Amino acid sequence: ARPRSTRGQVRLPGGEFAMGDAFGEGYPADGETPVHTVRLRPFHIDETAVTNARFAAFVKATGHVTDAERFGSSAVFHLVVAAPDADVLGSAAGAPWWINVRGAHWRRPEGARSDITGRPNHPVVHVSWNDATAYARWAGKRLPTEAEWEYAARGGLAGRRYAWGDELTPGGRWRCNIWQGRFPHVNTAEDGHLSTAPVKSYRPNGHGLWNTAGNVWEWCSDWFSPTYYAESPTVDPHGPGTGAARVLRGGSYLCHDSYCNRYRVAARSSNTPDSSSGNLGFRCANDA
Ligand SMILES: [Ca+2]
Image 1 (tube, rainbow, N blue to C red):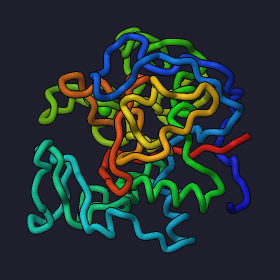
Image 2 (image 1 turned 45 degrees about the vertical axis):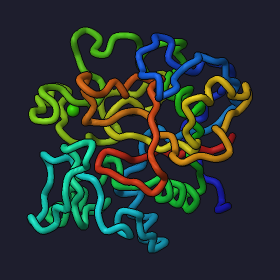
Image 3 (image 1 turned 180 degrees about the vertical axis):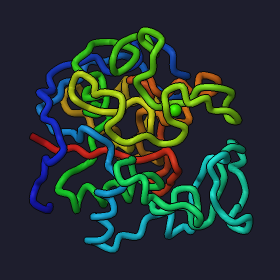
């Protein structure tokens, strides 16, 4: 391990909390139930998702090549594709709004005709689980467990639907970056952002974490299993020992009811560790 750094991290006391979907709003294969008691020891977690600027420092220091670069392409939402026609490789068979764009990666998130010069304080995207874990190691940190992630995101509140409470738009107003309008064709940007927002935007939750709901998906250390909640230990669960996909949490700027409720604090998903997309980043953590 590199010398530890809790820079840009808040220390949370842990303790017991009720992990899982209280409301039964996820779909069966997500395994958000049963609601089960988890006991966490005190730990540190990034107040924000990792930014473009910090990931640049990592790459400058290490020469890290991301999976998206190695594979040669990454998934870009159809509306923002900024590339020559020859770099469009085809849409995702299952999700036609996801475009496979040659050369799309963290530096050029919409393809070769894009850059991040205006987005240093935006979350880094097109980063795989591998990229995320490599960053954390150089940075003197780790990824949070899924349990740590949910605890931190709940912000000291018990059994709420969202990081801040049960109403999605309290007082009719937005405090997270998701999708409003006719998905996947029209984004009304009611929440003030079409694509990613700065990592500190809106306001923090009760634990001082910003944007755990929406903006970008966030990789956790755990292997995903839809039955793990039923077989989880009480103290510091790390997920199952083997698996195919790693856990991601939070939902993104592309989330809308019609197909997605993933901004709920208890919502969970997963992806193969080497996968990447323009709506998927991460935040780091540490033991106390
Ligand atoms: Ca938005």
